[PDB]
Image 1 (spheres, helix red, strand yellow):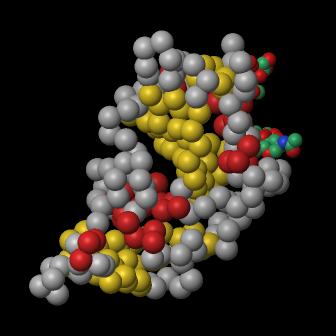
Image 2: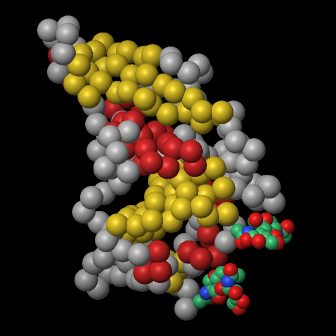
Length: 209
Ligand SMILES: *[C@@H]1O[C@H](CO)[C@@H](O[C@@H]2O[C@H](CO)[C@@H](O)[C@H](O)[C@H]2NC(C)=O)[C@H](O)[C@H]1NC(C)=O
Ligand SMILES: *[C@@H]1O[C@H](CO)[C@@H](O[C@@H]2O[C@H](CO)[C@@H](O)[C@H](O)[C@H]2NC(C)=O)[C@H](O)[C@H]1NC(C)=O
């Protein structure tokens, strides 16, 4: 069989967390250890699987999400934290095994370029018709924030805010968001989210033996 193609991850400027890029793999062979050996891995944690198991099992699919992400914001990735990252930007499946990897890009990994800064959504909210009540708009597993329609791929200025008037068909009211920025680090720091699914006789994403 053919090798899983991880090259988009290694090519060009990775998106910000709320614009995470998604790679989907079926029917291919992988070597996770080899992929990760290109990076300096700072954190590698999983739910319903382990770092050793995720590198050595056969799956019906493997999903890999990737983005620029400052290591300083480690804690904001957890569901248990009610931080803006897990609330408004990026959420992994709660029903399939997952891993989250935080890594630093070495200088000798040249095909990856730095963005100007890190950006994230600090707030995504709906104003109701009473013009008073704001309802947080929590990102769903496997989806973008509804606010990706109004927040640009790079936040221009820390504290910028954004609104969209919604149609009766969309439930009326206003979608409202605010963006934050974090200074670029000496070396680019990234997050990788891996989600796996197991099937019956379709477990064809397998490690290189
Ligand atoms: C998958 O990739 C890993 C990492 O490149 C391979 O293990 C390394 O390669 C050689 C194998 O002779 C060892 O000497 C190193 O100590 C290993 N770790 C490194 C380089 O970090 C591994 O062989 C590959 N697995 C398969 C099944 O091909
Ligand atoms: C490219 O950069 C990598 C990433 O840091 C270098 O690998 C490191 O080498 C040092 C010692 O030389 C180790 O202590 C680190 O643990 C290594 N990093 C990783 C992620 O394994 C590597 O030496 C450089 N390679 C080239 C060809 O320049």
